[PDB]
Length: 131
Length: 171
Length: 244
Image (cartoon, rainbow over all chains, first blue to last red; front, side):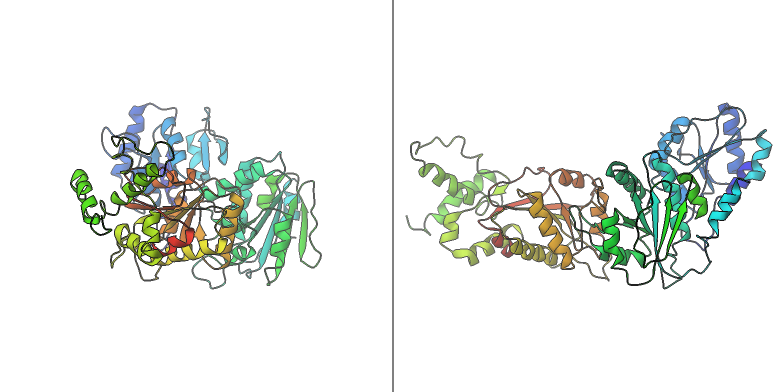
């Protein structure tokens, strides 16, 4: 959460002055769904409102929520649950997409027509000061 | 060091002021076959973000002119089709299918805030739009192996790069 | 009998058989029934046919030409007679996606096409700066070479008739959404659909009510039936100007 708040504070500008808001997209891998939903619950409890393409229980993946939440000022960032949600979101975004990876041992596979960076940190603690 | 050649290429030819005047800036780039489609877009977006001021505050908007060469039209249109998908709206003097070259569309897009940059297909369209923009025109060349001929009555810079990757941090 | 005597008689059988309105029977079905009566009367060998398959021939979506309705009343009445029947105008023209499909052949001069396009664009668009829902007609041409079609497109752009075709740059794929934004664009006068492949992909991108106005001479394209269509057949392309 210290990394996510640092990601949200820098690479999101949701002030009322501008007319072009933007929010980052967050992806996590290599974890079980127990602590992934556990992290997801506290972020929403701390008024860091996000969208993951599942606006209700038992929903199919709806990337149109990720479309509007990117331009919404009251939605701070965007969560991506898994690989299949990430690839489907990529086709739904038509504007320019840059993907930044912060990994330790396992590297995700990323489609090659996107601008990618790959950063191998010592562990998760070193990610926050970079971002 | 290594970044010394980048500093020898950055502020000595493509120095940038914070209040640069609306000039007809031409950017000629070497799109050879070994260059990926994706890495050109990083240069196009860097050129558009720096050398265009399409904000609603100003009353003198300007947009850069982009020229590509060294490859066939298969990847030139494929690069052209991607840039329109990512809401980077441009014009090339061909507003409809089967059109003749209309340099007037390039003039209005230069002053248009909703048109981000201007595309030039080849040298024949480059020379035709050369006589259309009355205001001062500056041409910047970034190339690896071929240097094209620009008429000598324009301010030109010539920059030799190792590949297309180093052009973006120059601009 | 007399010309007037059988006029009120012949429409009466068709009126209760199909249970439609006056213009859908006297103007739409009775007009087509006169030609195919004459089409077998002027046949050299088979003059008398069975009429079992006649009643479905004339209920096509098309409105065929009637040369005998051209020669008797002249071009002033007949084109007005076609205009009042199927192209009933209102005071407030709603922002509908109107498609104007006109047959283009090499016997047609390039000048008289533009005056038909200028008539369609002026009568079927509201590009005012004050309207909240601007609309602009869609233009489709067929039957002609692409070299003659591009000459018409290039001439219209030089006369400050700005249009979009779904091809915003050279080598572009067809972008159907450009015509939708051009429908709501006050600085785009009309839309130029290039061919029939670009036509059917445009209906799938529009959700508002769509009307199709087809004006051919010899060949009429197959249009989906659920779309409201007006397929009027004319002699020459200059007659299309006086009906739209």
